[PDB]
Image (cartoon, rainbow, N blue to C red; front, side, top):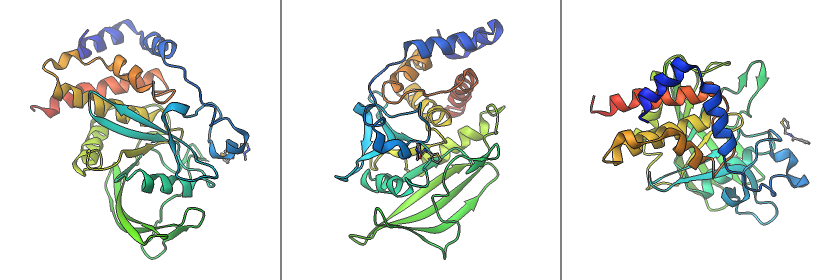
Length: 284
Ligand SMILES: Cn1nccc1C(=O)NCc1cccs1
């Protein structure tokens, strides 16, 4: 079926939970043996969220190459994304090592450091220009260059230096700051505006390594971001945009990381975002 009318048909029939459970039943199951080794327990935020072995990002290190991060490679859309958990106190150096080694231009953050009165990820970037951060375990230096605070998101320019070679690179930090502590946003308008700002920066384009996207577990809000982006790109590429099947795209992405889209409310929000986004693209 088309998307917008499949949408109203699920609303009128109140069957979002049943649709979402079907997706969960059909999703791929692949091994995640490296994630479950005992030496990696303090590298995982949640015991039930792990990268598959076949798609995990490897650190360029001979001691321990493990990070909780996955490469989502979308062949028809010609887009790739790295989805990862919010960094932990003992993995902030690994996180920036990955950004460096994978040649990423941008980092997309969809959570606040504290939500619901608890810490959802480490404070992994510097908050003042004159107070830079040094990660001694991976030999990197990170400096805040500029910060632009808007009503729904903040954009930061960061300098990442590899202290071993003295090479430097500019990294863009796109921080969506207004996702509610409970539920999903009422309107997708500010989330779509944010996605378009990430696109306009070049961070999603083929001349750079894959964008790094995270929330707390790296599967819920993070899944919504890449699902909406890929679906809109396919609607632009195909002769028949109504052929794009958001459930099929989501199942394809779940071949690369488990659990993408965590609730039926996030599934409905993803439909809403793609539907509204397709009108603004045109041609309107
Ligand atoms: C050390 N350890 N033993 C078992 C599990 C862990 C662990 O590091 N878990 C992740 C988190 C640490 C602190 C906040 S979340």
